Image (cartoon, rainbow, N blue to C red; front, side, top):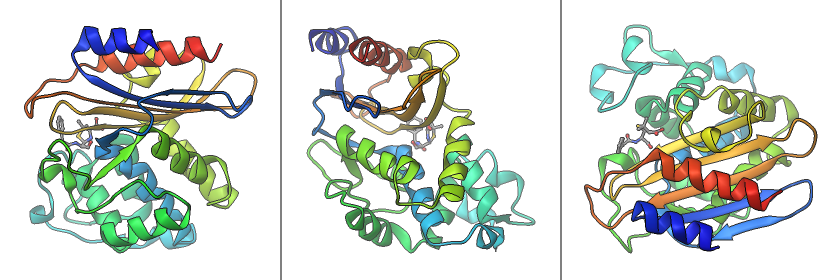
Length: 257
Ligand SMILES: *C(=O)[C@@H](NC(=O)Cc1ccccc1)[C@@H]1N[C@@H](C(=O)O)C(C)(C)S1
């Protein structure tokens, strides 16, 4: 409690923390219901919904696109404009590289932010507010609730898809594999977790120094932890520091042990 305030003190930032130990039902909450721009963590839920709406076979559908559908951070999708990419390959790119264009293509496919919100409401997430495609292209100003969620809701919806019954097991397995194989999170939740332990995570970064990671974390032996660490700062062009996330993860891990 004061460890998390210490981190807020040390990094001049606001933290939102929610963790669930699914083995004991122990919880670690710190501003659990405070809203942050969810930023690219929404990609994990976007794929959950894609997977609910498609057989694994249907993920082989090819999606074509041009250079004009690519804006900022498209490491995978910029390599394939000639051929396009299948839904499967877009999911991989979106989750493991946070390919922004891949995300936009998947979001279109599922019916846009309106359909994403519909499906999240259906799983009992009253908080996550998808509003815009690309939502990184627009600022979430303090007090704005469009494209925001909370640590607690993000954990709840992530557990629903990844760990519970919102997906049949072969699709839940695909989601988990992609997340475990994320390339973008080494300095975040993964840097705060004990060595060896498996981590499936999805990162995000926006304006106002927003720096997020959501994860499922497995102990050698036992049930997983599901965790959201959301952060933001006072100023629109504020810098973030990944260390804040890693260190907040350390505190959660302490508290769970
Ligand atoms: C979603 O979070 C994406 N963010 C952006 O495109 C905007 C942005 C804002 C500030 C700094 C950098 C980028 C992509 N996801 C993150 C992430 O997964 O950490 C990237 C920084 C890779 S871009």
